[PDB]
Image (cartoon, rainbow, N blue to C red; front, top):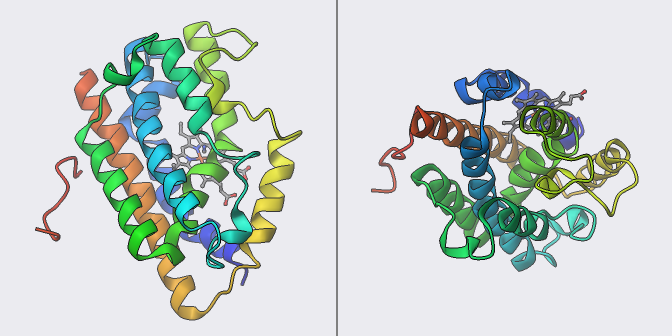
Length: 222
Ligand code: HEM
Ligand SMILES: [C-]#N
C-alpha cells in the first residue's frame, strides 16, 4: 500500500472529527469574525514557521527530501504578508502565541530535530489540506469577511507558483510514495499524522474558547 493511501485512510476518521469541531462548524457557518480569523492565521504563522524551519534542516535527508518543494508549497512568506494585512506594520510583536500553538510548535521541533522520518506526517497533514479543503475554507472566508478575489488577507490560501493545486497534490502524493518505506516507518508516520490532526483540533478548540513532565498532557488538551 502506498504511503499516500495509508495516510489518507489513517486520517479519514480524525479528519471528520476535526471539520466538525466547534470552531470549524462556526467557521463553515460564516460565524467567525476578524478577531477569530486573526487568531487562527497568527497561530498558523508560528506553526508553518516551525514546520518549514524543520523542513530546511532536513532538506537533504532522504526521509523527506523528495518532498522539498519550497517554491510551490511553503506558506511562511504568504503568512507574513497576511500578518501585515491583518495586524499591520508591527505585526511582529502584535500577534499572539497561544498555548496550543506553542505545543504544536514544540512537537514539530521534536520531530524535525529528533524524528525527521516522521516530518512527512506533519507536512502531509497541513499542506495536502491547504491544497484541497483549504480552498473551500478560502471561499468561506472571502464570503464571510468580504475579502477581495484579488487575494489580500488570504495569501496563505493562494499558491501563485502552482497552476492547479489539485494537480500539484497529485504530484506530492506520488513523491511521498517514493520515500523509503518499511513497516516501522509506515506505522509511525500514520500514527504521527493522527497526532498532527489532534494538535490542530486542540488549537481550534482553544481558539473557540478564547473567542467565547514529557508525559504531562498539553494545557490545550481536549
Ligand atoms: C472546516 C473544516 C474542513 C473542511 C471543509 C475540509 C475539507 C476537505 C476536503 C473537501 C478535502 C478534499 C477531499 C477530496 O475530495 O479528496 C480535504 C482534504 C484534506 N484535509 Fe481537510 N477539511 C477541513 C479541515 C481540515 C483540518 C483541520 C485538517 C488538518 C490540518 C485537514 C487536513 C486535510 C488533509 C491532510 C487532506 C488531504 C487528504 C488526502 O487526500 O489524503 N482538513 N479536506
Ligand atoms: C482541508 N483543508
